[PDB]
Amino acid sequence: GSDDGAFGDIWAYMSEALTGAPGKIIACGMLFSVAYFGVVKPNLGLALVSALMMLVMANGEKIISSFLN
Amino acid sequence: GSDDGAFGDIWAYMSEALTGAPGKIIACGMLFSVAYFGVVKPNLGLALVSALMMLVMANGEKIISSFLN
Amino acid sequence: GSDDGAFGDIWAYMSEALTGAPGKIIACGMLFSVAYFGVVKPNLGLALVSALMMLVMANGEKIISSFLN
Amino acid sequence: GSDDGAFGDIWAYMSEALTGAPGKIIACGMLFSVAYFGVVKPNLGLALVSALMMLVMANGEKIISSFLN
Amino acid sequence: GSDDGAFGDIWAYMSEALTGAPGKIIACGMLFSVAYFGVVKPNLGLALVSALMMLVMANGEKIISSFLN
Amino acid sequence: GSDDGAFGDIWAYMSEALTGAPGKIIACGMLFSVAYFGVVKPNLGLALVSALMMLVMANGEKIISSFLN
Amino acid sequence: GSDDGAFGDIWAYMSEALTGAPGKIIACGMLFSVAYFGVVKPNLGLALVSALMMLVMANGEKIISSFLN
Amino acid sequence: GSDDGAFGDIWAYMSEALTGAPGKIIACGMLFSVAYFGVVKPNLGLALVSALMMLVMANGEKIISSFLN
Amino acid sequence: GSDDGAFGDIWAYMSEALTGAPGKIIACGMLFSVAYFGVVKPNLGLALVSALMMLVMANGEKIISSFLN
Amino acid sequence: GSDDGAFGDIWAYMSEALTGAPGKIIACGMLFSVAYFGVVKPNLGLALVSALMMLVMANGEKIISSFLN
Amino acid sequence: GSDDGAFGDIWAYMSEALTGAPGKIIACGMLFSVAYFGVVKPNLGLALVSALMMLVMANGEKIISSFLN
Amino acid sequence: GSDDGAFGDIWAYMSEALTGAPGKIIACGMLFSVAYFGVVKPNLGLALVSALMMLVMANGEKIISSFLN
Amino acid sequence: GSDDGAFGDIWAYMSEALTGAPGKIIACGMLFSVAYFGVVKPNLGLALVSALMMLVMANGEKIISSFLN
Amino acid sequence: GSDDGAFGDIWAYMSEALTGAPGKIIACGMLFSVAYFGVVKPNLGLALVSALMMLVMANGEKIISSFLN
Amino acid sequence: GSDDGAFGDIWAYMSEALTGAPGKIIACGMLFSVAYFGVVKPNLGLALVSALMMLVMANGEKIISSFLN
Amino acid sequence: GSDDGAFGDIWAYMSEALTGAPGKIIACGMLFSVAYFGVVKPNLGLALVSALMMLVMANGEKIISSFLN
Amino acid sequence: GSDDGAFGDIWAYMSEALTGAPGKIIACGMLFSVAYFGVVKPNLGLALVSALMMLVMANGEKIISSFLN
Amino acid sequence: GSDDGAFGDIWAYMSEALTGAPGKIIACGMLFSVAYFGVVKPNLGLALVSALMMLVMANGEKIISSFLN
Amino acid sequence: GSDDGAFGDIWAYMSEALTGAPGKIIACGMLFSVAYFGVVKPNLGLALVSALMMLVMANGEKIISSFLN
Amino acid sequence: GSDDGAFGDIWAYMSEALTGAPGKIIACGMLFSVAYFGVVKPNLGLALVSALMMLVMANGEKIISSFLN
Ligand SMILES: CCCCCCCCCCCCCCCC(=O)OC[C@H](COP(=O)(O)OC[C@@H](O)CO)OC(=O)CCCCCCCCCCCCCCC
Ligand SMILES: CCCCCCCCCCCCCCCC(=O)OC[C@H](COP(=O)(O)OC[C@@H](O)CO)OC(=O)CCCCCCCCCCCCCCC
Ligand SMILES: CCCCCCCCCCCCCCCC(=O)OC[C@H](COP(=O)(O)OC[C@@H](O)CO)OC(=O)CCCCCCCCCCCCCCC
Ligand SMILES: CCCCCCCCCCCCCCCC(=O)OC[C@H](COP(=O)(O)OC[C@@H](O)CO)OC(=O)CCCCCCCCCCCCCCC
Ligand SMILES: CCCCCCCCCCCCCCCC(=O)OC[C@H](COP(=O)(O)OC[C@@H](O)CO)OC(=O)CCCCCCCCCCCCCCC
Ligand SMILES: CCCCCCCCCCCCCCCC(=O)OC[C@H](COP(=O)(O)OC[C@@H](O)CO)OC(=O)CCCCCCCCCCCCCCC
Ligand SMILES: CCCCCCCCCCCCCCCC(=O)OC[C@H](COP(=O)(O)OC[C@@H](O)CO)OC(=O)CCCCCCCCCCCCCCC
Ligand SMILES: CCCCCCCCCCCCCCCC(=O)OC[C@H](COP(=O)(O)OC[C@@H](O)CO)OC(=O)CCCCCCCCCCCCCCC
Ligand SMILES: CCCCCCCCCCCCCCCC(=O)OC[C@H](COP(=O)(O)OC[C@@H](O)CO)OC(=O)CCCCCCCCCCCCCCC
Ligand SMILES: CCCCCCCCCCCCCCCC(=O)OC[C@H](COP(=O)(O)OC[C@@H](O)CO)OC(=O)CCCCCCCCCCCCCCC
Ligand SMILES: CCCCCCCCCCCCCCCC(=O)OC[C@H](COP(=O)(O)OC[C@@H](O)CO)OC(=O)CCCCCCCCCCCCCCC
Ligand SMILES: CCCCCCCCCCCCCCCC(=O)OC[C@H](COP(=O)(O)OC[C@@H](O)CO)OC(=O)CCCCCCCCCCCCCCC
Ligand SMILES: CCCCCCCCCCCCCCCC(=O)OC[C@H](COP(=O)(O)OC[C@@H](O)CO)OC(=O)CCCCCCCCCCCCCCC
C-alpha cells in the first residue's frame, strides 16, 4: 500500500504512538495490573505474557506494513 | 465485471485504500485494542486473529475481483 | 519511541509511580497478603516471589523503554 | 522512588501498620494458629517459621524501599 | 511499632487472650490430647513438648513486640 | 468527618446495629455454621476465627470513625 | 449493644435455639457422625472434640453478648 | 434449652434413634468390621473400643441434654 | 483547579461527605458484608481490604485535589 | 488553532472546569462509586483506574491543545 | 406512619398474607427446593437457611412497622 | 397466620404433597442417587443424611405452621 | 424551602405516605420478593439490603427537607 | 442579569419552588421510585444518585444566577 | 401421606423399580466395581458394604413410606 | 479440494506459517511455559508433550490436505 | 432434491469450498488454536477433536446430499 | 519453515531469549526453588532435574527448528 | 546467550543474590532445620546434604551460564 | 557474596541467632531429649552426637560464608 494521502498523517501518528507515549502508558498499565493481581495470587507468568505483548507492540508497525503493502 | 465507468475512480480509490493508509489505520487500531484489552486479561490469541484479519484485508481486492468479475 | 507529546506527562507520572508511592503501596499489600496467608499455612516462598515481583517492578520502566523505543 | 505525592499518606500508613497494630494482630494470629495446630500434632518448627515471618515483616519496609527507590 | 490506633483494642485483646482464657483452653486441649494419645502409646515426651509450647505462648507477646516495634 | 447531617440518623442506626441485634444475629449465624460444619469435620479453629470476627465487629465503629474523621 | 428493636425477636429465637432443639439436633448429628466414622476407624478423640463443640455452643450466647455489647 | 418447638419432633426422633434401630445398626456395623479386620490381624482391642463407643452412644442423649440445656 | 464557582458548594458537600455520614454508612456496609459473608466462609482478609478501602476514602479528597489542581 | 473568538469564553470555562469544581465533583463521584461497589466485592483495582482517569483529566487540556492547534 | 387510608386494606392484606397462605406456600416451596436439590448433593444447611428465612418472614410485619412508623 | 383464603387450596395441596406422592418420589430419587453414587465409592453416610432429610420433610408442615402462624 | 403553598397538601401527603401505607406496602413487597427469590437460592443478604432500604425510607423526609430547605 | 422586570415574579416563584414544595414533591417521587425499583433488584446506589440530584437542586438557583448574571 | 393422585403412577413405578430391574442393574454395577477394584487391591469389605447397600435398597420403600405418611 | 481460488493466497500463507515464524513463536512459547512451570514443580513430561505438539504442527498441512481434498 | 436451478452455482461453489480453500483455512485455524491453547495447558485431545471435525467436513457434502435429496 | 517475514523479529527475539536473560532468570528461579524446598526436605535429585531442564532449554531452538522447518 | 538487555538487571540481581544475602538466609534456614530435626532424631548426614546444597548454590551461576550461553 | 542489601538485616539476625538464644534453645532441647530417651534406654552416644551438632551450629555461619561468598 501507500503511506501517504489524506490519511497519511493519521497513520504516521498512530504508528509512532504504537511505540510512543500511548504504547508506553499501556505497557505500564499491564505492569501495574500484573503487580496488583500478584498481591493475592503471585504469578510471574503474566509478566512474561506482558513482555511478549510489549515485544508484539514493538513489531506492530512492521507486521502491519508487511501485511498491508 | 468491469473496473471502469462512472464509478471506476471510486472503486480504484477504495481498493487502493483497503491496503493503504485507511487499512493501516484500522490495523493499528486493532493492535491498540489488543494491547489495551490485554492489560487486565493478557490474551495473545486476539493478536493472531488480528493478524489473520490483516491477511484477509491484504487479499480483499483479489477476493472481490474473483467473486465479482 | 518518543517520551514526549500530548501523553508525555501521563507516561512520566505512570513511570515515576511504578517505583513511587503506588508501587510501594502495592508491594506493602503483597507483604501483608504473605503475612496473612502464612497464619494458617506458613510459606516463605511466597515472600521470595513477592521480592522477585518487586525487583521486576523496579526494572519495569527499563523493560518498557527497551521494548518500546 | 518518591515517598510523597497524592498517595504518600496511604503509603506512610501502610508502612507504619506493617510493624504496627495490624502487623502485631497478624503475628498473634500466627502464634494462636501454631498453638492450636500443636494440640494434636505438637510441632515447634512452625513457631520458628512464624518467628522468621515476623522478622521478615519487621524488615518489609526496608525491602520495599530498597527495591522501589 | 505503635500499639494504639484503630486496631489498638483488637491487638490488646488478642495479646491478653494469648495468655488468658483462650490460651488456657488451648493448653488444656493439648493436655487432654496428650492424655488421650497416651492410652495406647504412653509417651511423656509429648507432655514436655506441650509444656514448651505453653512457655512459648507465655512469651508470645514479648516476641511479637520485639520483632514488630 | 461529621456524624450529623441528613444521613446522621442512618449512620447512628447502622453503628448501633453493628453491635446490636443484627450483629448478634450474624454472630449466632456464624456459631450455627461452625456447629453444623463440625458434624462431619470437627474443626474448632473456625470457632476461633468466628470469635475474632466478633471482636472485629465490636471494634468496627471505632475503626470506621478513626479512618473517616 | 441492645437486645431489643425490630430484630429483637429474631435474635431471641436464634439465641434460644442455639441451646434448644436445633442445637440438640446438630449435637445428635455429630454424635451419629462419630459413631458412623468409628465403624471402620474407631476414634474416640472425635467424641471429645464433639463434646468440646457442645460446650462451646452452650456458651455461644454468652460469648456473643460479651463481644457485641 | 427447650425440647419442644417446631423442631421438637425431629430432636425426639434423633434422640430415640441414637439408641434405637439406627444406633443398633451402626453398632452391628462396628462389630462386623471388627470381625472382618481380625481375619488377617486378630485384634480384640478394637472390640473394646467398639464397646466403649456403644457405651458413649448409650449416654449420648444425656451428654447432649447436659451441655445444651 | 479552583474550588469555588457555581459548583463550589456541591464539591464542598461531596468532599465533606466522603469522610462524613455517607462515607461512614458505606464503611459500615462493608463491615456488615464482611461479617455476613464470613458466616459460611470465615475470611478476615476481606476485613483488611475493607480497612484499606476506608483508608483510601480518608485520603480521597487529597488525591482528587492533587490530581485536579 | 486559536483560543479566542466568539467561543473563546466557553472554551476557557470548560478547560478551567475540567480540573475545577465539576471535574472534582466527577472524581468524587468515581471515588464514591468505588467505595460503594466495594461493599459486596472489594476491588481496589477500580481505585487505580479512577486515579488514572483523574490523571487523564488533569492532562485533558494539554492533550486537546496538542491535537487541536 | 399510619396503617389506615386509601391503601390501608392493601397493607392489611399483604401483612396478613406474609404469614398467611401465600407465605406458607413460599415456605413449602423452599422446603421442596431443599428436598429436591438434596437428591444429588445432600445438604441440610440449606434447611437451616430456609428455617431462618421463615423466621424472618414471621417477623417481617414487625420489622416493617418498626422502620416505617 | 390463616390457612384459608384465595390461596388456601394451593397451600393445602402443597402441604399434603410434601409428605404425599411428590415427596415420596423425591425421597426415592435420593435413595436411587445414594445407591448409584455408592457403586464406585460405597458410602452409607449419605443414606443417613437422606433419612434425616426425609424426617425433615415429614415435619416440614409443622415447622412452616409454627414459624408462620 | 417552604412546605406550604398550592402544592403543600401534595407534599404533605407524599411525605406522610413515604412512611405510611404505601411505604409499608412497598416494604412488604420487598420482603415477599426476598422470600420468593430465596426458594431456589437462599440469600439472607438481600434481607439486610431490604432492611437498609426501609431505614432509608424512614429517613427520606428528613433527607429531602435537609437538602431542599 | 437582572432579577426584576415583567418576568421577575415568575422567576422568583420558580426559584423558590425549586427548593420548595414542587422540588420536595419531585424528591419524594425519586425516593418512592428508588424504593419501588428496589423490590426486585435492591440497589442503594440509586439512592446516592437521588441524594446527589437533591443536592444539585438545592444549588440550582446559585448555578443559574452564576451562569446568567 | 397418600400414594395416589396425579403422581401416583410415577411413585408406584419408582418404588417398584427400586427393587426391580434398575435396582438390580445398580447392584450388579457395585458388584462389578468391587470385582474390578479388587484386582490390584483385593478388599472383600467393600463386598460387605455393597451387600448392606443392597439391603438398604430392599427396605427403601418401607423407610420412605414410614417417614412420609 | 482445490488449493487455488479467491482464498488460495490466504490458505498458502496460513499453511506456510503453521511451520513458519508464527508456529516457531508458538513452539517457543510452549518451551518457555514448560521452563517456567518447572521452577516449582519440575516436570519433563510436559516437554515431551510439547515436542509431540510440535511434531503434530509439522504434519498439520499434510493432515489438512489429506482430510480436505 | 435437485442440484441445478437459479441457486445451482451457489450450491456448487459452497460444496466445493467446504473441502476447498475456505475449509482448509478453517482447519488450519483449528490447528493454530490447538497449538496456541496447548502452550499453557498441553492437551492433544483437542487435536483429535479437530481431526474428527476435519473428517466431518470432508463428508459434509455427502451428508447434505443424503439428507436433502 | 521460514525464519523471516512479518514475525521474524519476534521469533528471533524469543529464540535468543530462550538462552538469554529471561532463560537465565528462569533457571536461577529453579535453582532458588530447589534451594528453598531443600531446607525442610533436602533433595538433590530436583537439582539434577533442573539441570536437565536447563539442558533442554539450551537445545530448545534446535528442537523447534528441527520439528518446524 | 547474552547477559544484557531489558532483563539484564534482573538476571544480575538474581545471580548475585544466589550467593548473596537471600542465599545465605536460605542456607541458615537449612542449618536451623538440621539442628531442629536433630533434637529427636540426631542425624548429621542431613548436615552433609545441606553442605552439598550450599556448594551447588555456590556454583549455580556457573552451571546456568554454561547451559544457557 | 555480599552480606548487605535489602535482606542484610535478616541475614545478620539469622546468623547471630544461630549461636544465640534460638540456637541455645534448640541445643537445650536436644539435651532434654537425650535425657528423656535415656530413661528407658541409657545411651550416652546420643549426647556425643548432640555435642557434635552443637559444634556444627557454632561453625554454621563460617561454613555458609565460605560456601556462599
Ligand atoms: C488499613 C490497614 C493496612 C492495610 C492492611 C491490608 C492491606 C491489604 C492487603 C492484604 C490483604 C490480603 C488478603 C486479601 C483477601 C482477598 O481475597 O482479597 C480480594 C481482593 C480482590 O482482589 P482481586 O480483584 O485480585 O481478586 C479477585 C478475586 O480474588 C475476588 O475475591 O484483593 C484485594 O483487593 C487485595 C489487594 C489490594 C492490595 C493492593 C492495594 C494497592 C492498590 C490500591 C492503592 C490505592 C489506590 C488508590 C486509588 C485512589
Ligand atoms: C477472640 C479470641 C482471640 C483470637 C483467637 C484466635 C485468632 C485466630 C487465629 C488462629 C486460628 C487458627 C486456626 C484457624 C482455622 C482456619 O482454617 O482458618 C481459616 C481462615 C481462612 O483463612 P485463609 O483465607 O488463609 O484460608 C483459605 C482456606 O483455608 C479456607 O478454609 O483463616 C483465618 O481467617 C485465620 C487467619 C486470621 C488471622 C489473622 C487475623 C488478623 C487479620 C485481621 C486483623 C483485623 C482486620 C480488621 C479489619 C477492619
Ligand atoms: C467437654 C469435655 C472437655 C474437653 C475434652 C477434650 C477437649 C479436646 C482436646 C483433646 C482431643 C484430642 C484428640 C482429638 C482427635 C482429633 O483428631 O482431633 C481433630 C481435630 C481437628 O484438628 P485440626 O484441624 O488440627 O486437624 C486437622 C485434621 O487432623 C482433621 O482430622 O482436632 C481438634 O479439633 C482438637 C483441638 C481442639 C483443642 C483446642 C480447643 C481450644 C480452641 C477452641 C476454644 C474455643 C473457641 C471458642 C470460639 C467461640
Ligand atoms: C430458625 C433456626 C435458627 C437458625 C438456625 C441456622 C441459622 C443459619 C446459620 C447456619 C447455616 C450454616 C450452613 C449454611 C449453608 C449454606 O450454604 O448457606 C448458603 C447461604 C448463602 O450464603 P452466601 O450468599 O454467603 O453464599 C453464596 C453461596 O454460598 C451460595 O451457596 O448462606 C446463608 O444464607 C447463611 C448465612 C445467613 C446467616 C446470617 C443471618 C443473619 C443475617 C440476616 C438477619 C436478618 C435479616 C432481616 C432482614 C429484615
Ligand atoms: C433419620 C435417622 C436419624 C438420623 C441419623 C443420621 C443423622 C445424620 C448425621 C450423621 C451422618 C454422618 C455421615 C455423613 C456423611 C456425609 O458425607 O455428609 C455430607 C453432608 C453434607 O455436609 P457438608 O455440607 O458439611 O459437606 C460438604 C461436603 O462434605 C459434601 O460431601 O453432611 C451432612 O449433611 C450431615 C450433617 C447434617 C447433620 C446436622 C443436621 C442438623 C441440621 C438440620 C436440622 C434440621 C433443619 C430443619 C430445617 C427446617
Ligand atoms: C448384608 C450383610 C450384613 C452386613 C454385613 C456388613 C455390614 C458392613 C460393616 C462391615 C464392613 C467393614 C469393612 C468395610 C470396608 C470399608 O473400607 O468401608 C468403607 C466404607 C466407607 O466408610 P467411610 O466413608 O468411613 O470411609 C471413607 C473411606 O474409608 C473410603 O474408603 O465404610 C462403610 O461404608 C462401612 C460402614 C457402614 C456401617 C454403618 C452402617 C449403618 C449406617 C447405615 C444404616 C442404614 C442407613 C439407611 C438410610 C435409609
Ligand atoms: C437496617 C440494618 C442495618 C443494615 C444491615 C446491613 C446493611 C447492608 C450491608 C450488608 C449486606 C451484605 C450482603 C448483601 C447482599 C448483596 O448481594 O447485595 C446486593 C446489593 C446490590 O449491590 P450492587 O449493585 O453492588 O450489586 C450488583 C449485583 O450484585 C446485584 O446482585 O448490594 C447492596 O445494595 C449492598 C450495598 C449497600 C451498602 C452501602 C449502603 C450505603 C449507601 C447508601 C447510603 C444511603 C443512601 C441514602 C440516599 C438518600
Ligand atoms: C519477551 C520475552 C520472551 C517471551 C517470554 C515468555 C513468552 C510467553 C510464554 C510463557 C508464559 C507461560 C506462563 C504464562 C501464564 C499464563 O497464565 O498465561 C495466560 C495467557 C492466556 O492464555 P489462554 O487464553 O490460553 O488462557 C486462558 C486463561 O488461562 C486466562 O488466564 O497465556 C498466554 O497468553 C501465553 C501463551 C502465549 C504464547 C503464544 C505466543 C505466540 C502467539 C502470538 C504470536 C504473535 C502474535 C502476533 C500478532 C500480530
Ligand atoms: C544435565 C545433567 C545430566 C542429567 C542428570 C540427571 C537427569 C535426571 C534423571 C535423574 C533424576 C533422578 C532423581 C529425580 C528426583 C525426582 O523426584 O524427580 C521428580 C521429577 C518429576 O517426575 P514425575 O512427574 O514422575 O514425578 C511426579 C512426582 O514425583 C513429583 O515429585 O522426575 C523427573 O522429572 C525425572 C525424570 C526425567 C527423566 C526423563 C527425561 C527424559 C524426558 C525428557 C527428554 C527431553 C524432552 C525434550 C522435549 C523438548
Ligand atoms: C516428539 C517425541 C516423541 C513423543 C515423545 C512423547 C509423546 C508423549 C507421551 C508421553 C508423555 C508422558 C508424560 C506426560 C505428562 C503429562 O502430564 O501429560 C499431560 C497431558 C494432558 O493429558 P490429559 O488431558 O489426559 O491430562 C489432564 C491433566 O493431566 C492435565 O495435566 O497428557 C498428554 O497430552 C499426553 C498424552 C498424549 C499422548 C497421546 C497422543 C496421541 C494423540 C494425538 C495423536 C495426534 C492427534 C493429531 C490431530 C491432528
Ligand atoms: C529478589 C530475590 C531474588 C529472587 C529470589 C527468589 C526467586 C523466586 C524463585 C524461588 C521461589 C520458590 C518457592 C516459590 C513458592 C511458590 O509456591 O510459588 C508459586 C508461584 C506461582 O507459580 P505457578 O503459577 O507455577 O503456581 C501455580 C500455583 O502453584 C499457585 O500457588 O511460583 C512462582 O511464581 C515462582 C516462579 C517464578 C520463577 C520464575 C521467574 C522468572 C520469570 C519472570 C522473569 C521476569 C518476567 C519479567 C516480565 C517483564
Ligand atoms: C560439601 C561437602 C562435600 C559433600 C559431603 C557429603 C555429600 C553428601 C553425600 C553423603 C550423605 C550421606 C548421608 C545422607 C543422609 C540422608 O538421609 O540423605 C537424604 C537425602 C535424600 O535422598 P533421597 O531423596 O534418596 O531420600 C529420600 C528419603 O531418604 C528422604 O529422607 O539424600 C541425599 O540427598 C544424598 C544424596 C545426594 C548425593 C548425590 C549428589 C550428586 C547429585 C547432585 C549433583 C549436583 C546436581 C547439580 C544440579 C545443578
Ligand atoms: C527468627 C529466628 C531465626 C529463624 C529461626 C528458624 C528459621 C526457620 C528455619 C527452620 C525451620 C525448620 C522446621 C520447619 C518446619 C516446617 O514444617 O516448615 C514448613 C514450612 C513450609 O515449607 P514448604 O512450603 O517447603 O513446605 C510445604 C509443606 O511442608 C507444608 O507443611 O517450611 C518453611 O517455611 C521453612 C523454610 C523457610 C526457610 C527459608 C527461609 C529463607 C527464605 C525467605 C528469605 C526471606 C524472603 C524475604 C522476602 C521479602
Image (tube, coloured by chain):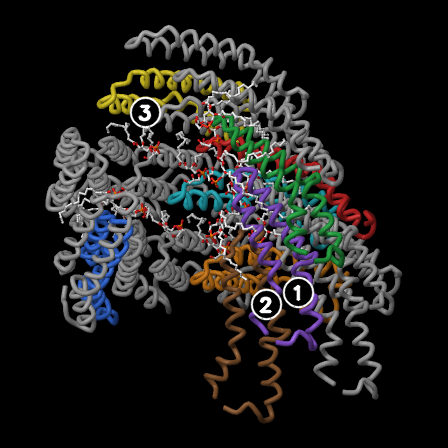
Chain colours: C red, E yellow, I cyan, L blue, N orange, P purple, Q brown, R green
Q: Which residue was labeled with disc 2?
A: P64
- Characterize the local packing of mark 3: few (<14), some (14-19) or many (20 or more) Cα atoms within 10 angstroms: few
Q: Which mark is residue P15?
A: 1
- Characterize the local packing of mark 2: few (<14), some (14-19) or many (20 or more) Cα atoms within 10 angstroms: many
Residue C18 vs residue L5: left or right? right
Q: Which residue was labeled with disc 3?
A: E25
The tag earlier along the polypeptide, 2 or 1, is 1
Question: Chain for mark 2?
Answer: P
Looking at the rendered structure, the kind of residue marked 1 is Ser
Residue L45 vs residue N16: left or right? left
Label 3 beta carbon within 8 A of ligand 3: yes
Horizontal and vertical percent for residue Q4?
57, 92
Disc 2 from disc 1: Cα separation? 9 Å
Name the quadrant containing residue L12. Answer: bottom left
Residue E17 vs residue P22: left or right? left
Question: Chain for mark 3?
Answer: E
Disc 2 from disc 3: Cα separation? 71 Å
